[PDB]
Amino acid sequence: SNKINDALNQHYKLNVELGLVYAHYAHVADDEFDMPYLGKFIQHLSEDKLGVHKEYISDYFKRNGMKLKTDVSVAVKSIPSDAKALIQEVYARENEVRDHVKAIAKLALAEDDYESFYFIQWYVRDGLKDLTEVDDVVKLFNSSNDKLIIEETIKEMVEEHEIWG
Amino acid sequence: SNKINDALNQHYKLNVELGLVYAHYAHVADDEFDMPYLGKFIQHLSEDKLGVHKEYISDYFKRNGMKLKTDVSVAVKSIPSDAKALIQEVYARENEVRDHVKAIAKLALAEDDYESFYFIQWYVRDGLKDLTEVDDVVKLFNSSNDKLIIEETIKEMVEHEIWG
Amino acid sequence: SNKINDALNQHYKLNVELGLVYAHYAHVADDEFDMPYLGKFIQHLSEDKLGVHKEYISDYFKRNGMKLKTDVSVAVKSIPSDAKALIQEVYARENEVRDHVKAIAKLALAEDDYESFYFIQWYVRDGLKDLTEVDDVVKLFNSSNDKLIIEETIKEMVEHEIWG
Amino acid sequence: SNKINDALNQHYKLNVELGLVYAHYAHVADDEFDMPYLGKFIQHLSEDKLGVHKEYISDYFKRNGMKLKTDVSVAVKSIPSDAKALIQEVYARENEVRDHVKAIAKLALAEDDYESFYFIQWYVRDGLKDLTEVDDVVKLFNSSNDKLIIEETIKEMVEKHEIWG
Amino acid sequence: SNKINDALNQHYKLNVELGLVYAHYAHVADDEFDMPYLGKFIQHLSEDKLGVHKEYISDYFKRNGMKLKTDVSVAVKSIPSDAKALIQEVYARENEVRDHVKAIAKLALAEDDYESFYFIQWYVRDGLKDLTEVDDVVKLFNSSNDKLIIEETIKEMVEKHEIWG
Amino acid sequence: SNKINDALNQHYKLNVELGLVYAHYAHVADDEFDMPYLGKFIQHLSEDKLGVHKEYISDYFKRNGMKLKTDVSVAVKSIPSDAKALIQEVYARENEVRDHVKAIAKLALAEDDYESFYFIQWYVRDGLKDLTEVDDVVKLFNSSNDKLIIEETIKEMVEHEIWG
Ligand SMILES: [Fe+3]
Ligand SMILES: [Fe+3]
Ligand SMILES: [Fe+3]
Ligand SMILES: [Fe+3]
Ligand SMILES: [Fe+3]
Ligand SMILES: [Fe+3]
C-alpha cells in the first residue's frame, strides 16, 4: 500500500525533527535557566524520539516491503523566555503528535490493512504515556516558586503500568 | 573566542548530518543488498555519530560559556549500485571528517587557546580510529566474491594502548 | 631552561597562598554565616590546593633537575560580608589561575620544551574542572533564598571522560 | 579569655610555618643527598603538621567562640650541609615546640580554664611522641657510615603504646 | 609526509640497535662483574626497547599509510671497565634518545600534522620515565662500597604515578 | 673448547638476523597482502627467534665459561610478490637452520664433548617442530582459492610426548 507508506514516512520525519528540537531545548534549559535536571528530562525525551520511535518504523518497512524516504529541515530561531513556557511548548508538541497518530490509525483501519493497525497500537499507547509523563512535570510550576524545590522533585523523578506500560 | 565557536558549531552540524545519512544507508543496505550485518555495522557508526560526538561539544559549550545554534538540512537522492560503492562512500566521508578536525585544531593553536586544543585531542584520536575501522571492512570486498563469507567475517568483527 | 623554572616557582607559591586563604575562608564561612557544608566544600578546595597541586611540581623538579625556592607571605585581613560575595571571590581566584596557567603553557611551547607541555596539560584540564565545580555553587545563590535548602543541596553535592 | 586566644593563634602560626619548612627539607633531602626514604619520613612529618595539628585548633575555636587570625610569612635562605645536620635541625624544632606547649599549658591552668587544659593535653602527649620518633632516626647516624643500610632501616621503619599512643 | 616518515624510520632503527647493545651489556655485566641483578635490570631495559618501542611505530605505519625500512648494523667492540662505567653508558644512551624524540616532535608540530604529534606524546613521556628509572640506579654506586648491598637494593627494586607512569 | 664456541656464536648471530627479517615480513604480509592473521603468525615466529632461541645460548655461555660476541648486519630489499611466495621463503629459511644445527651437533659429538650434545638436543627437536608447523600452513595455499577461507583457518590455528 502507498497511502500508509506516505503517512508512516511523515511520522518518521516528524519524530526526527522533534528529537533535534528537544535536544536544543535541553541544552538551552540547562545553560541559561540554571535548571540542570529539567535538561536531563528533556534530553531523555530527545533520545527516545531519535531511537526506537524511528527504529520501529524502519524495521517495519524492511519487514513488509515498503520504501523509505528521508528529508529533514530544522532550525531553532526563537527560544521561550523562561522554563514554564518551555515545558508548555513541549506539552503542545506531544499533544499534536497524538493527533497525528490518530489520523494514521484511522487511515489504516479504512484501507483494510490490519497489520498496520496492530503495528500502530504501540504508538497509540506510548503517546498517552509520554504525554502524562510530561504533564506531571508541567504541574510542578503551578505549585511552588523555589526553583530548587522543583529541582529536587524532578531529580527524584529522573532517579510500570499493566495497561499503559 | 569567536573563530573556535564558529568552527565547533559547524562541526556539530556536520556530525548531525552524517548521523542521519548513515542511518538511511544502513537501512538501504539491510533491505536492498541482502546484507544484514553490514547494516548493523553502519547503524552502529550512525549511533556513534549521533551520540557522544555531539554530546561532548554541547557539554563543552556549557562549561566554557559559548553559544549554540541548531540548523540542519539533509535529503539523500543518490544511492550507489552495490555494497562496495556504499562502503567506499562511507570511507570518503570519514576521511573528510579527519580533514575538518585537522583544520579546527590548527585554528585553535593559532588563537593561543589551549583548552580548545586539549578538547580536540579526543576527536583527533577518534578520527583515525574510525577510519581504520571502516577501511578494515573496505578491504574485504577486494579479497573474495562470495557474499556469505564476507557476511560471516563482518559478523565476527562486530561480535590499543595509544588509540584507546 | 630557566624561564620555565621561574614560572613554575611562581605557580608553586601561588598555590600555597591560595590554600591558606581558602582554609581561613572555610573557617569563616562555617563559623560566621552558619553554613557548615559550604565550609566543608571550601575545605576540600583548600586541601586540593595544598596537596597534589604542589606535589606534582616538586616531583617534576626532582626529575628534570630544577632548583626549588620557598618564599611565601600571606595575611587575611578583609573578608566579604555574606556567603554570596565569598563564593564570588572564590570564583574570581579560580578564573585568574586559569589565565596564569595559560601563560605558562604558551611560554613552554614558545621555547621548544615539550616535556613541560605534556606536564602542564594536567593543570590546563584541572583549571576548567575546578572552575565548573565552583560555578555550579555560585549559581545556587540565585535559585532560592531559603538558606537551609542551599545547605541540603550542597550536602547532596559533596566524572566526564574528557574533563576528568 | 584573651591570653589563651593569643597563645593558640601563635601555635597555629607556628605549626603552619613548620609544615612549610619541613616540606622544603624533605625535597632537599630527596634531591641532593640521595636518601629518598628520609624524604618520605620528613614529608610525613610535614603533612601531619599541616593537617590535624591546625584542624583541631580551628575546630576548637569554632566550638567555644574565639576568633582566628591568619598571618604567615616564612622563607628559606639557608640549608644544612648533609643529612645529619638536617635531621638535627628537625630535632631542634620539635624540642622547641615542646617548650611552647608547656608554656601554653601553664598559662591555661593559671586562669581557671580547664576546658583548654583538657584540650592541650593532646599536644602535651604528641610532642613527646614526635620527639621520640625523630630521635630514633637521628641516632642511626651514630651507628654507621654506609648510607644504604641506613636507607634499609629507615624503609623498614616507615613502611611497617597504651600511654603515649 | 616524507619528513615524518624518515624520522620515524630512523627511530625504529635506533631502537633495534639499542636493544641489541643493551642485551650484550646485560650478559657481560652478569658474567664478568658478578652482578646478576644489574644484569636482570639491563635485560629488562633491553627487551622493553625491543618490544613496544618499535611495535607501536610499525602499527602507526600500518594505520596511516607510510612505508617501513629495515637497516641494522651493530658491533660492540669495546666494553666498559667496571659496573659504574656501564651504568653511566646506559644513562647517556637514554639521555640522547630523549632529545632525538624532542626533535621528532618539533618537526611534527611544524608541519601541520597533529596525528603524529598526538602519537609521539607517548615517547615524550616514556623518555623521561626510563631516564629517571635508570638514574635512581646509577645513584647507588655513590652511596656505598661493597657490592652485595647494592645487589640487595637492586633486588628489592626489580622485585616489585598519575602523570609520568 | 673453541670450535663449539665459534659455532654457537655463529648460531646466535643467525637467530638474531632471522628474527629481524621475520618481523619485517610480518609487517609486509599484514599491510600489503591484506591477511592480518598470517601477520600474527609470522610475528609469533619472530618473537620466538628473538627470545628463548638466544637467551638459552647466553645462559649456557654463562654456565660453562665460553665468551660471547655480537655482530649483526641486516638490510631487507626484495620481498616476494604475494603471500604464497612469502610463506615458501619462510619454509626455506627454517629448512636451512635445521641443517645448521645438525652440523653443530655432529661436531659436538666428534670433539667428545657431551654437555654440548645434551644442550643441542633441544634445538635438534625444536627445529623439526617449527618446520612442521610452518609446512602445515604452507600447504593451505595449495588447497583453495579464496583468501578469507585461508584467513579463517589460520585464525583457528592461532587460537606431543616426543616433539613437545
Ligand atoms: Fe516514547
Ligand atoms: Fe567516533
Ligand atoms: Fe583541583
Ligand atoms: Fe603530631
Ligand atoms: Fe620504555
Ligand atoms: Fe623454535
Image (tube, coloured by chain):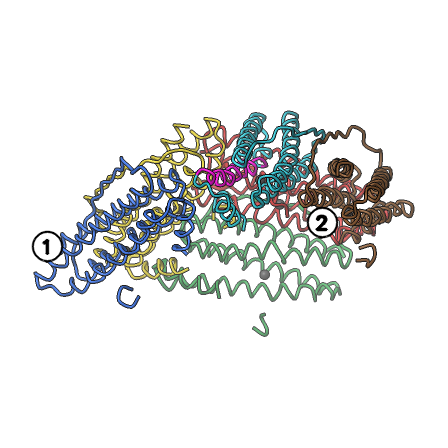
Chain colours: A brown, B cyan, C red, D green, E yellow, F blue
The residue that disc 2 covers is: C26
**What's under tag 1, amino acid-wise?**
Lys
**Mark 2 or 1, closer to the camera:** 1
- Residue D71 falls in image quadrant: top right
Q: Residues within 10 Å of mark 2 (few under 14, many from 20)?
A: many
Which SS class for mark 2?
A: helix
The residue that disc 1 covers is: F3
The front one of F47 and B135 is B135
Left-right relation of B21 to F127: right
Left-right relation of C59 to F68: right
Magenta residues (range): B119-142
- Confirm if mark 1 falls within 8 A of ligand 6: no
- Residue B102 falls in image quadrant: top right
Tell me, yes or no, if residue A83 can be seen here: no
Query: Does the magenta stretch mainly form a helix, a strand or a loop?
Result: helix
Q: Quadrant of ligand 4?
A: bottom right
Q: Chain of mark 1?
A: F
Residue F36 numbered tag: none
Quadrant in which the N terminus of chain F is drawn: bottom left
